[PDB]
Image (cartoon, rainbow, N blue to C red):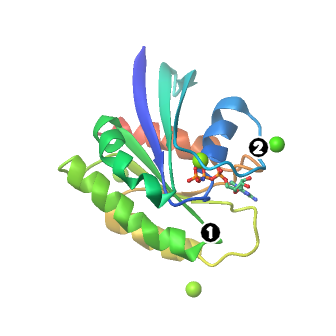
Amino acid sequence: MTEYKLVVVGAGGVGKSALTIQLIQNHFVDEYDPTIEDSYRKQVVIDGETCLLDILDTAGQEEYSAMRDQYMRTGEGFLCVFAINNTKSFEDIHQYREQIKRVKDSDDVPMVLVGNKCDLAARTVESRQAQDLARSYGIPYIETSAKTRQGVEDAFYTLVREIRQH
Ligand SMILES: Nc1nc2c(ncn2[C@@H]2O[C@H](COP(=O)(O)OP(=O)(O)NP(=O)(O)O)[C@@H](O)[C@H]2O)c(=O)[nH]1
Ligand SMILES: [Ca+2]
Ligand SMILES: [Mg+2]
Ligand SMILES: [Mg+2]
Ligand SMILES: [Mg+2]
């Protein structure tokens, strides 16, 4: 079966772990335990194809920015996550996409822009603003909530479908 190497990146606290754990383990992590670097692996059927998702849940704490080059090298596709109630996390996306872009020496790396926490009402990043960013990258924008499960499968499966276009 086909393996897909996914990597989840974004600022601290945007919900990278919560999203990954919701996808893989089907529950919502309420508490906030900052991540160093964890791996998750799960066999799933996507569009009729049995495949193995290998997902690297990375650190948003800038203290660990040194580890980015390593995982950006190995990853096949990147879930670039910000929170819709965290304007700064949205502005931070560019610096993640720039690094991925450099490391893969490519303007063409399978990526999905994800606006997480869409269950919360304190929105400061409007859908249209994120759509414009994703458009400029030539990638999809998808809103998610790790809490309600909204968009969670859509985000990760879309990332698989982007890798397949590569
Ligand atoms: N309401 C709501 N809270 C969320 C959502 N996703 C994450 N959170 C909350 O936000 C906090 C941080 O989540 P977490 O997944 O740990 O973020 P992270 O991006 O993995 N952090 P780090 O970069 O430090 O590893 C937690 O309290 C978590 O419950 C979401 O979709 N909705
Ligand atoms: Ca819980
Ligand atoms: Mg985390
Ligand atoms: Mg505004
Ligand atoms: Mg496309």
Element on which disc 2 rests: loop
**Label 2, ligand 2: CB separation under 8 Å:** yes
Q: Residue at x 49, y 27 (%)?
A: 53
Q: Position of residue 132 (x, y in %)?
A: 43, 73
Quadrant of the drawing holding the N terminus: top left
Write down the residue under mark 1. Answer: 84
Q: Residue at x 59, y 76 (%)?
A: 126
Where ligand 4 lies, by image quadrant?
bottom right
Q: Is residue 138 visible?
A: no
| CB contact under 8 Å: marks 1 and 2 | no
Marks 1/2: CA distance?
18 Å
Q: Position of residue 25 (x, y in %)?
A: 70, 30
Number of numbered callouts drawn: 2
Q: Which class describes the residues within 10 Å of circle 2: few (<14), some (14-19), or many (20+)?
A: some
Disc 2 residue type (three-letter) = Phe
Residue 4 vs residue 21, the one in the foreground: 21
Q: Which class describes the residues within 10 Å of circle 1: few (<14), some (14-19), or many (20+)?
A: many
Q: Residue at x 44, y 68 (%)?
A: 92
- Is residue 140 shown left or right of residue 108? right
Disc 1 residue type (three-letter) = Ile
Query: Which disc is residue 63 wearing?
Result: none
Image vertical order of residue 95 relative to residue 152, above or below: below
Q: Residue at x 34, y 37 (%)?
A: 76
> Which tag, 1 or 2, sits closer to the chain's start?
2
Element on which disc 1 rests: loop
Q: Which residue is farthest top?
A: 1
Write down the residue under mark 2. Answer: 28
Q: Is residue 145 visible?
A: yes
- Is residue 154 shown left or right of residue 75? right
Image vertical order of residue 102 relative to residue 84, above or below: above
